[PDB]
Amino acid sequence: SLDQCIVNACKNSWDKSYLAGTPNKDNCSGFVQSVAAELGVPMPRGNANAMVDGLEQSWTKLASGAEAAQKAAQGFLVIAGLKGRTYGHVAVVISGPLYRQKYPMCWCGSIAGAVGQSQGLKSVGQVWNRTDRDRLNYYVYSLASCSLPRAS
Image (cartoon, rainbow, N blue to C red):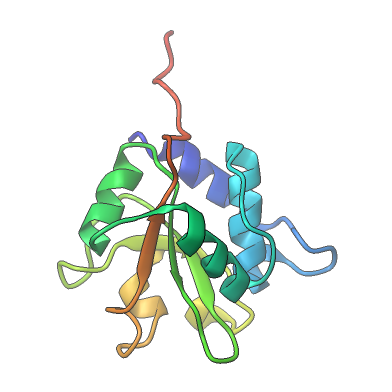
Protein backbone atom coordinates (compact mmCIF):
# COMPACT_ATOMS: atom_id res chain seq x y z
CA SER A 1 0.00 0.00 0.00
CA LEU A 2 3.08 2.23 0.14
CA ASP A 3 2.59 3.37 -3.46
CA GLN A 4 -0.76 5.01 -2.62
CA CYS A 5 0.75 8.52 -2.76
CA ILE A 6 1.99 7.75 -6.27
CA VAL A 7 -1.38 6.31 -7.36
CA ASN A 8 -3.05 9.41 -5.90
CA ALA A 9 -0.67 11.69 -7.81
CA CYS A 10 -1.47 9.75 -11.01
CA LYS A 11 -5.22 10.10 -10.44
CA ASN A 12 -4.82 13.84 -9.80
CA SER A 13 -2.57 14.34 -12.80
CA TRP A 14 -4.87 12.56 -15.25
CA ASP A 15 -7.15 15.57 -15.81
CA LYS A 16 -4.48 18.25 -15.43
CA SER A 17 -2.72 19.93 -18.36
CA TYR A 18 1.01 20.36 -17.74
CA LEU A 19 1.24 22.15 -21.09
CA ALA A 20 -1.64 24.64 -21.30
CA GLY A 21 -4.47 23.39 -23.50
CA THR A 22 -3.12 19.83 -23.76
CA PRO A 23 -4.72 17.30 -21.41
CA ASN A 24 -2.16 15.07 -19.69
CA LYS A 25 -4.18 12.06 -20.79
CA ASP A 26 -3.07 13.06 -24.32
CA ASN A 27 0.56 13.88 -23.46
CA CYS A 28 2.77 11.22 -21.89
CA SER A 29 5.51 13.59 -20.81
CA GLY A 30 3.04 16.11 -19.38
CA PHE A 31 1.37 13.40 -17.34
CA VAL A 32 4.68 12.33 -15.78
CA GLN A 33 5.67 15.98 -15.15
CA SER A 34 2.45 16.61 -13.21
CA VAL A 35 2.90 13.43 -11.14
CA ALA A 36 6.47 14.36 -10.26
CA ALA A 37 5.43 17.91 -9.41
CA GLU A 38 2.83 16.70 -6.87
CA LEU A 39 5.47 14.43 -5.34
CA GLY A 40 8.18 17.11 -5.21
CA VAL A 41 10.48 15.20 -7.56
CA PRO A 42 12.66 17.29 -9.90
CA MET A 43 12.42 16.24 -13.54
CA PRO A 44 14.12 16.90 -16.86
CA ARG A 45 12.08 19.21 -19.10
CA GLY A 46 10.73 18.35 -22.52
CA ASN A 47 9.02 15.64 -24.48
CA ALA A 48 9.34 11.92 -23.86
CA ASN A 49 12.64 11.56 -25.71
CA ALA A 50 14.08 14.53 -23.81
CA MET A 51 12.83 13.21 -20.47
CA VAL A 52 14.40 9.79 -21.14
CA ASP A 53 17.68 11.52 -22.13
CA GLY A 54 17.64 13.35 -18.80
CA LEU A 55 16.77 10.33 -16.67
CA GLU A 56 19.45 8.23 -18.40
CA GLN A 57 21.99 10.83 -17.29
CA SER A 58 20.88 11.20 -13.66
CA TRP A 59 18.68 8.37 -12.29
CA THR A 60 19.48 4.85 -11.16
CA LYS A 61 18.28 2.22 -13.63
CA LEU A 62 16.56 -0.90 -12.37
CA ALA A 63 17.28 -4.38 -13.69
CA SER A 64 13.76 -5.51 -14.59
CA GLY A 65 10.03 -4.82 -14.71
CA ALA A 66 9.73 -6.98 -11.60
CA GLU A 67 12.20 -4.77 -9.73
CA ALA A 68 10.32 -1.69 -10.95
CA ALA A 69 7.06 -2.93 -9.39
CA GLN A 70 8.94 -3.79 -6.18
CA LYS A 71 10.41 -0.30 -5.85
CA ALA A 72 7.02 1.26 -6.56
CA ALA A 73 5.62 -0.90 -3.76
CA GLN A 74 8.19 0.65 -1.39
CA GLY A 75 6.99 4.15 -2.25
CA PHE A 76 9.50 5.11 -4.98
CA LEU A 77 8.62 6.98 -8.15
CA VAL A 78 9.63 4.68 -11.01
CA ILE A 79 9.45 5.80 -14.63
CA ALA A 80 9.36 3.38 -17.55
CA GLY A 81 10.72 4.98 -20.70
CA LEU A 82 11.93 4.35 -24.22
CA LYS A 83 13.09 6.77 -26.88
CA GLY A 84 11.62 6.58 -30.36
CA ARG A 85 12.69 7.59 -33.85
CA THR A 86 9.98 10.23 -33.93
CA TYR A 87 8.28 9.96 -30.52
CA GLY A 88 9.19 8.30 -27.26
CA HIS A 89 6.91 7.26 -24.42
CA VAL A 90 7.07 7.46 -20.64
CA ALA A 91 4.89 5.92 -17.94
CA VAL A 92 4.68 5.72 -14.15
CA VAL A 93 5.12 2.17 -12.82
CA ILE A 94 2.86 1.14 -9.93
CA SER A 95 2.69 -1.93 -7.70
CA GLY A 96 0.51 -4.75 -8.99
CA PRO A 97 0.62 -8.16 -10.68
CA LEU A 98 3.09 -8.62 -13.54
CA TYR A 99 1.53 -9.27 -16.94
CA ARG A 100 3.02 -12.50 -18.38
CA GLN A 101 5.02 -12.58 -15.11
CA LYS A 102 7.25 -9.84 -16.55
CA TYR A 103 5.56 -6.52 -17.22
CA PRO A 104 4.43 -4.16 -14.44
CA MET A 105 1.23 -2.15 -14.29
CA CYS A 106 1.43 1.55 -15.11
CA TRP A 107 -0.23 4.90 -15.49
CA CYS A 108 0.33 6.98 -18.62
CA GLY A 109 -1.17 9.45 -21.05
CA SER A 110 -0.60 9.44 -24.80
CA ILE A 111 -1.21 11.52 -27.88
CA ALA A 112 -1.76 8.16 -29.63
CA GLY A 113 -5.06 7.79 -27.78
CA ALA A 114 -6.44 4.78 -25.93
CA VAL A 115 -3.67 2.33 -26.94
CA GLY A 116 -1.11 4.45 -25.11
CA GLN A 117 -3.26 5.38 -22.12
CA SER A 118 -3.43 3.53 -18.82
CA GLN A 119 -5.19 4.38 -15.57
CA GLY A 120 -3.40 1.64 -13.67
CA LEU A 121 -5.12 -1.17 -15.55
CA LYS A 122 -2.85 -1.74 -18.57
CA SER A 123 0.66 -3.13 -18.17
CA VAL A 124 3.73 -1.66 -19.85
CA GLY A 125 3.77 -4.88 -21.88
CA GLN A 126 0.42 -3.96 -23.43
CA VAL A 127 1.12 -0.22 -23.82
CA TRP A 128 4.35 -0.84 -25.67
CA ASN A 129 4.63 -2.96 -28.79
CA ARG A 130 6.03 -6.49 -28.50
CA THR A 131 9.25 -5.29 -30.17
CA ASP A 132 9.64 -2.52 -27.55
CA ARG A 133 8.41 -3.93 -24.24
CA ASP A 134 11.62 -5.87 -23.50
CA ARG A 135 13.71 -2.79 -24.36
CA LEU A 136 12.21 -0.51 -21.71
CA ASN A 137 14.32 1.42 -19.25
CA TYR A 138 13.12 1.65 -15.66
CA TYR A 139 14.38 4.67 -13.77
CA VAL A 140 13.98 5.02 -10.01
CA TYR A 141 14.32 8.22 -7.99
CA SER A 142 16.97 8.43 -5.26
CA LEU A 143 14.53 8.56 -2.35
CA ALA A 144 11.02 7.28 -1.71
CA SER A 145 8.47 10.05 -2.30
CA CYS A 146 5.63 8.41 -0.40
CA SER A 147 5.13 8.89 3.31
CA LEU A 148 4.70 6.95 6.50
CA PRO A 149 1.22 5.52 7.14
CA ARG A 150 -1.19 7.79 9.02
CA ALA A 151 -0.21 8.08 12.68
CA SER A 152 -3.90 8.25 13.70
